Amino acid sequence: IKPRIREILSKELPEELVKLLPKRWVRIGDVLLLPLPELEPYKHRIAEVYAEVLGVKTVLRKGYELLYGSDTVTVHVENGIKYKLDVAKIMFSPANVKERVRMAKVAKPDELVVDMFAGIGHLSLPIAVYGKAKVIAIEKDPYTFKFLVENIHLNKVEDRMSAYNMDNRDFPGENIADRILMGYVVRTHEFIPKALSIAKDGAIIHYHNTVPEKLMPREPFETFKRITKEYGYDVEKLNELKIKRYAPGVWHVVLDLRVFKS
């Protein structure tokens, strides 16, 4: 359908700009995230034809800026999982699909999983649905929490998945988790002491973080290990995966770690 768009726009666009039309886009549910600056004078006209041919209700600009339509709430379906969200307000990357598919395959059904940064259920919904485990999901932001709650119902896991709207440091659970999800990328090490308190002896922690290239592969395991030992714990690294690289040269990585007392 890439030709069909150009065909419609080559009859109103400057002819030299037709070669400059986005050849890629991010589609989340029924909502489109369209990248482009020289196309600015036609952004609304442009988004309107992408929506007509693609069959979406709304289009936002990445650079979120409304370009076509009004409704930014949608349900994205991925690996059988329903993720309702406000696209304009809540971060979700269809590009991180591999890690949510991985989460679908990790847990056993007798596990208790604690998701410390649940969002709308990004990493914990595949666990509740496919892995069948019990899950406690903590999300601090009230608006994001409403979608988390709605997604628990949409995915039919209200019997095994509990959500709380609070800061993860006020979560009073101690020594209870078989598995912890730390899917936050901003100086995630600051939350390690709380993770260790929530964890049972032998628990697996999926620790996300952002790391400068130059410090790899030493970091971020070296910092995690040093903090863990300071608090009187030990840690074994089972796996490390890179998820995505960002300018200038920083990586979103996930580490699968096993923690032990004494």
Image (cartoon, rainbow, N blue to C red):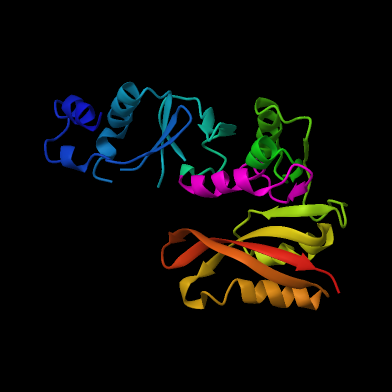
Residue 17 visible here = no
Closest to the observer, 234 or 211: 234
Is residue 106 a member of the stretch shown in magenta? yes
Residue 95 x, y percent position in the rendering: 46, 46
In the image, residue 136 above or below residue 237: above
Residue 154 visible here = yes
For the point 70% across and 43% down, the residue is 141
Closest to the observer, 37 or 233: 233
In the image, residue 92 above or below residue 220: above
Relative to residue 33, is residue 87 drawn left or right? right
For the point 63% across and 53% down, the residue is 183
Closest to the observer, 35 or 119: 119
In which quadrant of the rendered image does the N terminus lie? top left
In which quadrant of the rendered image does the C terminus lie? bottom right
Span of residues in magenta: 95-124
For the point 50% across and 44% down, the residue is 97
Residue 135 x, y percent position in the rendering: 76, 42
Relative to residue 166, is residue 213 drawn left or right? left
Residue 46 x, y percent position in the rendering: 28, 31
Quarter of the view holding residue 144 = top right
Relative to residue 172, is residue 189 drawn left or right? left
Quarter of the view holding residue 136 = top right
Is residue 260 a member of the stretch shown in magenta? no
For the point 80% across and 53% down, the residue is 177
Residue 82 x, y percent position in the rendering: 58, 30
